[PDB]
Image 1 (tube, rainbow over the protein chains, first blue to last red):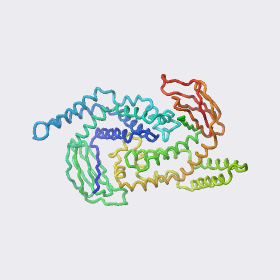
Image 2: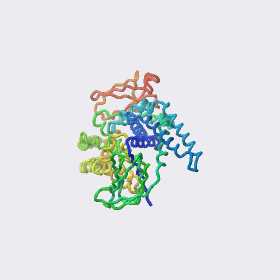
Image 3: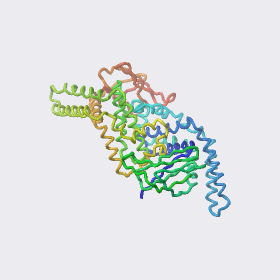
Image 4: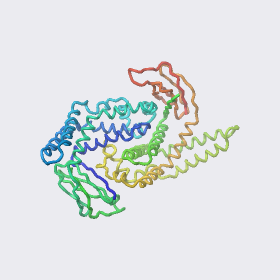
Length: 246
Length: 246
């Protein structure tokens, strides 16, 4: 049968962390950059990556979250009587993940400074503005050799290993913190108390012409399952879904 | 010779048609819409494309150009041995694209009225807002069956078939009405009058480490040839390039 995951942030920093995790993956979509399309896709996701670091301070809270997962993993270390080896190198994976970020360059500086990127990013604010005759540097850049762009791209993506990785760990260690408890929604409606929880990972069943519309006040969240167009396939119903509170 | 074709729009109206022709090309380029990237690339294009239409009325500008080129071809028909039926037959395509257009659903509406798009479009201005948790409605659309979207993609394309049929011809007739003269540039500089010309097609050479920086004063235009890399690789000398006033 058909299945779909629905991640949703329960707080203001997971929102940011997921936004970025999405932005960083997009850099790597295919990566034979060849066409106008190719380059723009990249720089928009980079510029958008940059726009976040205009605010936020993504370095400090990742650090603090890594110490959290350590203090978590700490809890499990002594007893129970299963897994010691894996978890220790898993902690040492965080210690090195944590360590490397703070001493690394002011995150995003390389691409912020970059000349080719500098140009395209100011022209990403006009509709159809970033084009051939508008970005004469871009237009030639594409005409250069096939593996010249690939030498500038890798360095472009590689500059954010301090951020990419640190995050990549933290988020794996979140997504495993909560098992999938099988719920049921009355009247196409549901509430609970998230608690400390950062994320919801809502698994949706038979594709009911429905999707999770989540709201929340303080710690408590309210899921309401909306259908695709109001009077198109209206079946609010009693749903039998699966939801984990990471 | 690894010739680097630089097209430059000398008037405000050509500047517009290039923006349009380029944005449409960026729809049909990728095509299957498998990924999230593949989505956002398509939806963002449309977004921007819709923002251009709300300016200047391209319907009532393009038609004036479809009316122009018709009369231009009509000059050649008088004589001599060169062409007769083949141009007469072409004129029927320009009458066709011209009327097909003059009687078409107000350009944009099918993509503004369609709900999924205008939703996505009001969120684009936010960096990384086009995210599963801020627009879950796109997640499902991207989880829908492999066949579903294609029919929905091909509609949104055909919505814009009247314009694409009209434009592509007007630009391709314009990129034919003139040939490539060979010209020279001292101290990386050039000046010349455009006159009746809508465009500058300009073939530089095998990446001479140079892009042209065209400016304008009325119908007069000037090229300041700039090199790659700032205070490093300045190589303007006397340069030998070729141009086309189209």
